[PDB]
Image (cartoon, rainbow, N blue to C red; front, side):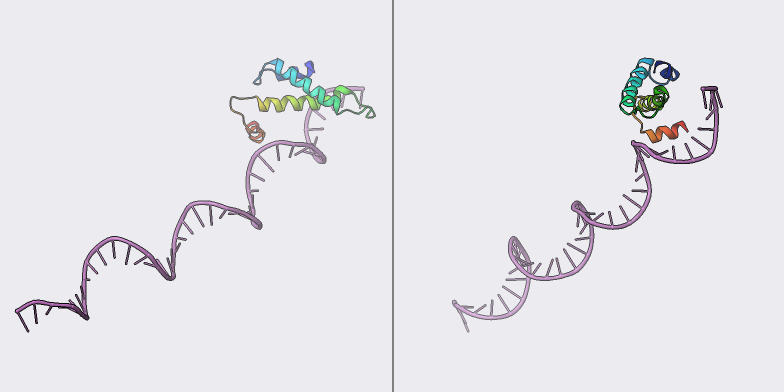
Length: 76
DNA sequence: GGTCAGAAAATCGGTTGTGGTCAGCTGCTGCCACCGGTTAACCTC
């Protein structure tokens, strides 16, 4: 999750917030994982980690909070 | 060459009445914000 989180430098927060959001995503994925998938755990959890990091970046991006749909159209 | 009495003001105050108008109230009308499922795009088991 450190190697996954390293691709989000310079976007609002420092690295540590991304690291801890990746830990949160790891907790959510390891709750939401099944052993009869026959899937690699990291390849499973990458979507969850990236989702958590991106939504926390959306939440804590700016001084004034902006809703995620306007964040999306700002990105667009 | 007086003398109550009536008619008719105005004046404060009810009244009725009624008409309307608007504050608001509130169940449809419909649009608008997350939520996530899916669907064609990248890296090579």
